[PDB]
Image (spheres, rainbow, N blue to C red):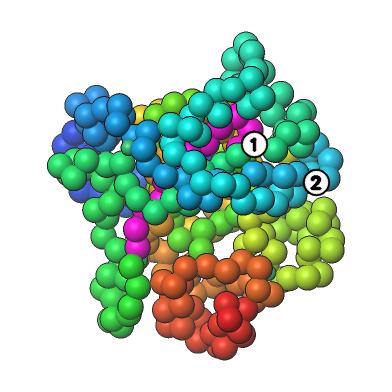
Amino acid sequence: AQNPNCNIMIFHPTKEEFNDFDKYIAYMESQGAHRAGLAKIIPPKEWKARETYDNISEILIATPLQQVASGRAGVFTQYHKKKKAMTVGEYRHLANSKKYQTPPHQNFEDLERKYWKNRIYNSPIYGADISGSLFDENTKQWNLGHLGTIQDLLEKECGVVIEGVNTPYLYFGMWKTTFAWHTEDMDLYSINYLHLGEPKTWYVVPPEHGQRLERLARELFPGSSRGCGAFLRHKVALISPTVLKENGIPFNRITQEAGEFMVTFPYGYHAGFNHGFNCAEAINFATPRWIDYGKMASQCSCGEARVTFSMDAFVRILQPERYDLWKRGQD
Ligand SMILES: O=C(O)CNC(=O)C(=O)O
Ligand SMILES: [Mg+2]
Ligand code: NI
Ligand SMILES: [Zn+2]
């Protein structure tokens, strides 16, 4: 078995290997990358997403989210308070303000220490989940707006034509902006490209150990657990690396820098934070290997997790028994 310790692997494809996305994902899996839940892909040196980022300031962040924490430093939840719209240029100024900027630090490790120590005492503002793309239309390789769609994958594998579309999302982050512990909708893959700015630190649990994380989460968030049998789908809970180590949960960590891709694999729980002003782009995708994960994915039916139009068909076709109850949660 390749990569039996479930380490995060880093890949350096050549320009020739960067042509065929599906084939490279399958290569990474042949080397055991999926066992970690997360892989880094450094693009060939010849590649670029677009020519410059000089003209992005007029993108609108229609609903910036203030991430308010409750709990203790290592075990907290966050809720998202909606703020007034602002442009990317306005957001970048805010991120760089004395109130919100990255503190002085020695290195990524020092910054990670400061994040875990102090995150709960601040409420950073995240421009998340903005439909759109920063890839130039002429970028032919690993262009997240030109991937094969999950609907077409399901059709190719299973023969059923379904409604739905699949488009990317932009994330504009600042210091301490945070992504809570989650897997993807329907335990899909995700791919994330850090277009610009400061890094993003990731934590991930190997898919084979996901249920260990879930069991800890039920212990640590006991009211949430009673409210919903899949409450990590709410994307609100954080658990520090110190706490994970104290409870014997297997995980790994890595920092993504501008110009790098990360891939999350089916049922790979992940969480993380941004180091400073940045912009990432991400999208879900599927492969043949995903189908069995989609069929087994947990679902939130309590009403909190509220998701896209396109998840309907996935539940309906892969999880027909669950469909009725899950749809009640959506309506
Ligand atoms: O970058 C973020 O805030 C969150 N991204 C992801 O969870 C992902 O790409 O799967
Ligand atoms: Mg603009
Ligand atoms: Ni994710
Ligand atoms: Zn729920």
The CA distance from mark 2 to mark 1 is 14 Å
Q: Nearer the viewer, mark 2 or mark 1?
A: 1
Q: Which residue is mark 1?
A: 124
Q: Which residues are magenta?
A: 166-177
Image point (27%, 70%), residue name: 152
Say left or right for 232 vs 202: right
Say left or right for 221 vs 24: right
Q: Vertical placement of 232 versus 59: above or below?
A: below
Say left or right for 161 vs 253: left
Image point (76%, 55%), residue name: 217
Quadrant hosting residue 9: top left
Residue 106 location (% of width, % of height): 62, 11
Q: Is mark 1 within 8 Å of ligand 1?
A: no
Mark 2 lies on a secondary structure that is strand
Q: Which mark is residue 70?
A: 2
Image point (35%, 63%), residue name: 166
Residue 226 location (% of width, % of height): 81, 70
Identify the amino acid type marked 2.
Answer: Ser
Q: Which mark is residue 303?
A: none
Residue 214 location (% of width, % of height): 71, 58
User: Is residue 26 part of the magenta span, yes or no?
Assistant: no
Identify the amino acid type marked 1.
Answer: Pro
